[PDB]
Image (tube, rainbow, N blue to C red):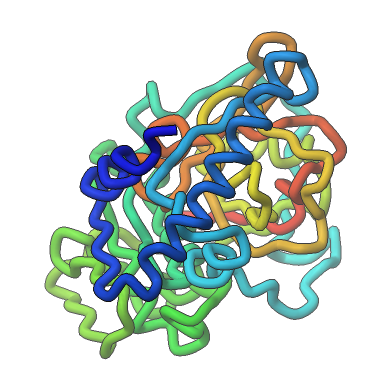
Amino acid sequence: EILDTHWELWKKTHRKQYNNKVDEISRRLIWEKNLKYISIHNLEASLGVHTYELAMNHLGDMTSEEVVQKMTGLKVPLSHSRSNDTLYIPEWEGRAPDSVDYRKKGYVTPVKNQGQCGSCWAFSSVGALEGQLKKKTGKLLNLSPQNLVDCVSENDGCGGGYMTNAFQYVQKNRGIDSEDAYPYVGQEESCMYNPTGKAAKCRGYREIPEGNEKALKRAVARVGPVSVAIDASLTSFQFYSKGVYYDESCNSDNLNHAVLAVGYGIQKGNKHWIIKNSWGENWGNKGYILMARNKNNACGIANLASFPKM
């Protein structure tokens, strides 16, 4: 009931300003809605209606359609399907483990905050484009998603874009800078790539078969981090916190987010997919979210995946 005092706490805790009480008391009202949702959901879990738990994050004030409007970025491109093309990837008749995590392997890097910009496409590519720089150079550094943002003329930069276009670019341009020499700002600028700061390179990419969650599983185990696309326009997704994630409402045709599969595995009876995100370290479980695996292609986890070849 003392929500009055707390909202302030949750306010100060973050960078909540709200200049002019106009929107102030408004966002706070929405806060109560979400907070309300969490309460219910987390109760339906204790009973066993769901298999995951939710909690408040720096996105309490915002709303579902909002984030899906200013913190996504995916831009499903034109046709490409073939299943025998040049960039297609047909795993070889070998064997795949039972569970892998590319974090314990130091193949992944800390999570960042794309911010209020459709930099998901760049943050997603700048992730797999990293896991390789480790699996070939042995040294893992943090590339720059900004680089692509204001350089990949074929992508709406802060306005939207795809991944197979970044891999293509980073390559065709002869190299991608490094966040250490081109800092992300989250606003769209002028391509100021500095060759004198090459961090990685590309020689092509590969599109994982369409739908094959099995192909997704082997690719990650044989190649490493894999840039994937998903449907992140659900309240359950936005307030995730722990446990495997599965909402029977996620759509396989509404792809609006691009994340990174840092491996897979099973947990407490349910399989899963370990995914790194770009919504700050506060979101979910320190930045990653366990997404149901081998469960009818939830949120289209294996609908539009791909990775670069260093």
Which residue appears at 79% of the width and 77% of the height?
79
Which quadrant does the C terminus fall into? bottom left
Q: Position of residue 157 (x, y in %)?
A: 43, 81
Specify whether residue 42 is in view: yes
Q: Foreground: 258 or 170? A: 258
Q: Position of residue 272 (x, y in %)?
A: 67, 27
Vertical position of residue 97 compared to residue 67: above or below: above
Which residue appears at 34% of the width and 83% of the height?
150
Is 50 left, or right, of 130 in this rendering? right
Is 136 left, or right, of 82 in this rendering? left
Q: Position of residue 269 (x, y in %)?
A: 73, 10
Vertical position of residue 88 compared to residue 35: above or below: below
- Total tally of numbered discs in the picture: 0
Which quadrant does the N terminus fall into? top left
Which residue appears at 19% of the width and 69% of the height?
182
Vertical position of residue 155 compared to residue 301: above or below: below
In the image, farthest residue toward the front: 1
Specify whether residue 274 is in view: no
In terms of image quadrants, where is residue 106?
top left
Q: Position of residue 101 (x, y in %)?
A: 50, 24
Q: Foreground: 250 or 176? A: 250
Which residue appears at 60% of the width and 31% of the height?
39
Q: Foreground: 31 or 189? A: 31
Is 307 left, or right, of 278 in this rendering? right
